Length: 36
Length: 259
Ligand SMILES: Cc1ccc(S(=O)(=O)N[C@@H](Cc2ccc(C(=N)N)cc2)C(=O)N2CCCCC2)cc1
Image (cartoon, rainbow over all chains, first blue to last red; front, side, top):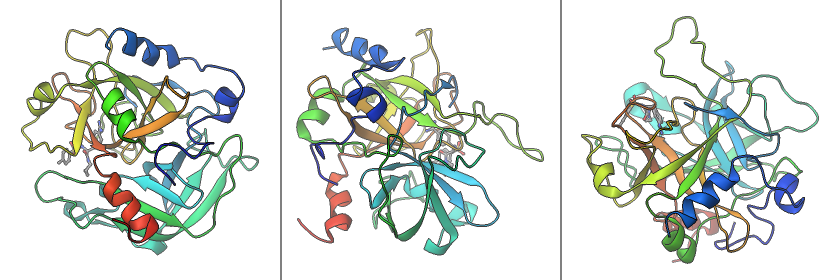
């Protein structure tokens, strides 16, 4: 466990590592540019 | 998950599942933050009013599922717990403040495509990313609607659910609930006009609320699904443990000491 990041952490194999966004991920990325 | 859609295989690879040794039920979500430790809501273990007090030899844990129901031999790993860590300042008899527990596993667990840790938030990630209107993600396997029960209910999924939910400003959180909200909690959910709905619910407690940084493309756990007055009631918000406000304690137990 560490703060900040395990190098490997929170980077999902089937998506992050595989150059692929999941299906409901741009909903989040949208909620940021509409926020600030 | 109220207003869930089925998960893609592999979407929350940190998602662990809590289970009673005998007879066999799902009790709470939880998350794998190391090969060694599972994070969850303290109420998964000690809620006195309801005879919840779980001994270490009463629970085992499941990592890497997709099905709620059928033992997926190829992918799934079953560990028993070596030790439990509920907080000494977990206030159950008032408002569940500091509803956070930890679970040390007896095996270290072996990561797969399908079994993998989330990141714990640091200062720059909490400060940046925890604002009102940024949505984060809730997963688990529990009810798609509120229930009492009969011989069972009806409203349990096949597959891990997702919903994505806005974090709600504090005034509107404070104001939603009769109940004393601390600086250790936050609420998520859609406000009344807002077109979309969705919530955690009985079965989803313990599970992770995660947020993905556009800085480094990774996930951080910011809440733990702590509580709610019902499952997705208009006017009412979903309550969550500010993991980071409690990063103090998380590392207390993991390093044994060290502030
Ligand atoms: C102080 C409090 C507030 C609400 C409830 S509850 O019975 O309405 N709702 C349940 C079930 C639940 C859990 C999570 C949620 C959620 N995060 N949306 C909603 C409902 C609850 O909060 N818990 C967790 C605590 C143990 C009892 C079960 C009970 C206690």
